[PDB]
Image (spheres, helix red, strand yellow):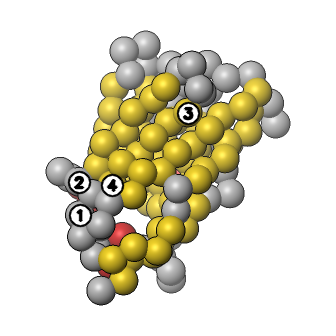
């Protein structure tokens, strides 16, 4: 209700390409609270991709994006970024950002009450 999230940066790319997604937060925000990216592929369920939380900005990454992803936050712009490199067709999905009133970055979608509408990433070969 009191925080809104808007994702951008999705597109159609070729296998191997990079994309930077952004999640812009507005409203009653607090930088240390967890911000997470999830993705949902066609015919599949939502799954954690990466997240950042805490006073020091500690990042966590899913096994699925090991060595291919970087998450960062810009407190001044109230924005969290996800850089994805070496994209593959299996990365095709709606990428959505989510937040919660805790610093803990968790992997279950069910524990985040606030979601953006998502941004689509489609990777062709």
On the image, the x and y values in percent for residue 98 come to 58, 44
Q: Is residue 21 left or right of residue 77?
A: left
Going from N to C along the chain, the mark reached first, 3 or 4, is: 3
Could you say whether the residue bearing mark 2 is in a helix, strand or loop? loop
Residue that badge 1 annotates: 86
Q: Disc 2 vs disc 4: Cβ atoms closer than 8 Å? A: yes
Disc assigned to residue 79:
3
- Residue matched to label 2: 68
Q: Residues within 10 Å of mark 1 (few under 14, many from 20)?
A: some
Question: Residue at the spot x=50%, y=82% of the render?
Answer: 43
C-alpha distance separating marks 2 and 1? 6 Å
Give the residue at the far left of this rendering.
Answer: 67
At 39% across and 33% down in the image, what residue appears? 72
Residues at marks 1 and 4 touching, judged by CB atoms closer than 8 Å:
no
Mark 1 → mark 4, Cα distance in angstroms: 7 Å
Residues under numbered marks 2 and 1 in contact, where contact means CB atoms less than 8 Å apart: yes
- Number of other residues with Cα within 10 Å of mark 3, as a class: few under 14, some 14 to 19, many 20 or more: some
Secondary structure, mark 3, is strand
Instruction: In this rendered view, identify the residue nearer to me: 108 or 8.
Output: 8
- Displayed quadrant of residue 79: top right
Q: Mark 2 vs mark 3: which is more N-terminal? A: 2
Q: Position of residue 3 (x, y in %)?
A: 74, 33
> Residues under labels 2 and 3: Cα distance?
20 Å
Question: Where residue 29 appears, x then y in whole percent?
Answer: 67, 23
Looking at the rendered structure, the secondary structure element under dot 4 is: strand
Q: How many angstroms separate mark 2 from mark 4 (CA)?
A: 6 Å
Determine which residue is flagged by label 4: 84
Callout 2 environment at 10 Å: few (<14), some (14 to 19), or many (20+)?
some
Relative to 34, residue 43 above or below: below
């Amino acid at each position: 209700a009191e925080v809104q999230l808007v994702e951008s940066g999705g597109g159609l790319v070729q296998t191997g390409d990079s994309l930077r997604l952004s999640c812009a937060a507005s409203g009653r925000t607090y930088t240390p609270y967890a911000m997470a990216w999830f993705r949902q592929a066609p015919g599949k369920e939502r799954e954690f991709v990466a997240g950042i939380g805490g006073i020091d900005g500690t990042a966590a990454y899913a096994d699925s994006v090991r060595g291919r992803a970087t998450i960062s936050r810009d407190s001044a712009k109230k924005t969290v970024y996800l850089q994805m490199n070496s994209l593959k067709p299996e990365d095709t999905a709606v990428y959505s950002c989510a937040t919660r009133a805790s610093m803990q970055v968790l992997t279950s979608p069910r524990v985040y009450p606030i979601w953006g509408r998502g941004t689509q990433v489609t990777v062709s070969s």
